[PDB]
Image 1 (spheres, rainbow over the protein chains, first blue to last red):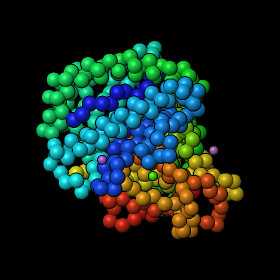
Image 2 (image 1 turned 90 degrees about the vertical axis):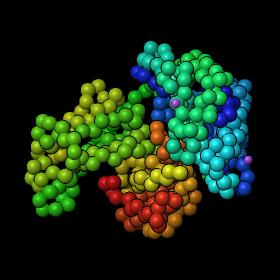
Image 3 (image 1 turned 180 degrees about the vertical axis):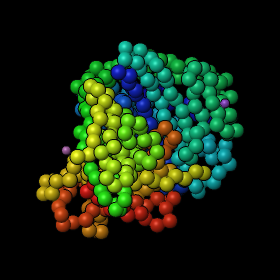
Image 4 (image 1 turned 135 degrees about the vertical axis):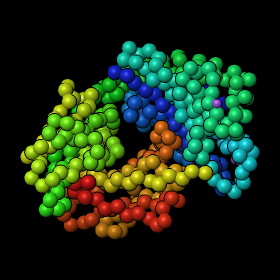
Length: 9
Length: 275
Length: 100
Ligand SMILES: [Ca+2]
Ligand code: NA
Ligand code: NA
Ligand code: NI
C-alpha cells in the first residue's frame, strides 16, 4: 500500500 | 514473529537525454512483491510475488497512480536540489527514498520510516517520534522549515500508523504460505590445505529464509570473533539465501573446531564439525 | 559527491552438479552510483542476454543487484563475471570456484 509521496523539497 | 514492509525508490537524472529514471520496489521482510520502472513497457505497478497477483483491478490503478505521482515528485525534487546545492544541469544525480513500517508478532504497530537521500548521503529523515524531522545539511534545513510549517509529519504519521500496518497485515495473511513459512539452512563442511602448517575450514549455509543467519566458529568451547572470514548473506535466485564462514586453523588441529549455526528455521541452533 | 566500490560475489544457485542445468549468479553490492556494467563469461567470452534483479538499496543508500543466466555446469568450460563501475580503475573479472 504505497504512500502519497507528493511534498516538494 | 516480527515483520516489515518497505518501499525503495530511486531517481537518476539524465543530463539532457530525456526524463530521469524512476525505479520503485516493494518488500515484505526479505521478499519483493511489487515493481515500477519508468523505462519498463507497462508503465504500471507490476507484481513480483504470486500472493499479490490476486489483488483487485482498482488496487493496481491506485498503486500505479501513487507511484506515478512519486516519480513526478522526485523529478521536481531533483530540480529543487540543483538550486539548493547550486549545481550544473550537465551532472547526473541520484535521489533515493525509503518508507515503510514494522509490526510485532501480534500484528500491531512497532516503528515507522520515511527518509530521503541526495547523491548517496542522507538528506531528510522522519524521527522515531513521527513528529519532527532530521536535516543532514543546510540545504535539507530549508526542507525542514517548509515541512514543519506545513505540518507534513502529521500526514506521514497518519500513513505509517494505520494505512501502512493494515497493508502489511493484509499482505501477511494473503501470503502466509510463503512469507510466514521459514526454511532452515542446508549446512555442509569443506577443507582446503593452502599450506603445510595451516588449513581452511568453510562452514556453508544454503537455501534459507529469512536472510538473518548467525554462523559462528569455535576453537574448543569459546567463539572465534576474529580470524573468521564471513561473506555477506547473498540471494540464491529463488526466495532463499546463501552465506558461509571460513577459518584458518593450524594443520592437524581440525578436531578442536566446531561451527555454530543460528536461524529461526531451526528448532535449536546447530553445532557442526569437519570429518 | 560520494562514490562506493562494488563488492562482487560469483556463485551458483544450487551446489555444483556436472551435466545438470543450474544458474550462474554475479551479485554486486554496496556500490554508488547505480550505473554498473555486469557481464557473465563462458571461457572468457560474454554470455548472451543475462537477466538481472530490480534495482534496490541497503540501509546506507548503497545499491545491490543480482545478474543471472540458465547455464549447464561441466568439468570443461570456465565461468567468470566482468564488473565495471565509475569507482573502478579497470573492469574486474572474478572467477567462479567450485567451493566459492
Ligand atoms: Ca536496465
Ligand atoms: Na525533466
Ligand atoms: Na535536524
Ligand atoms: Ni530452480
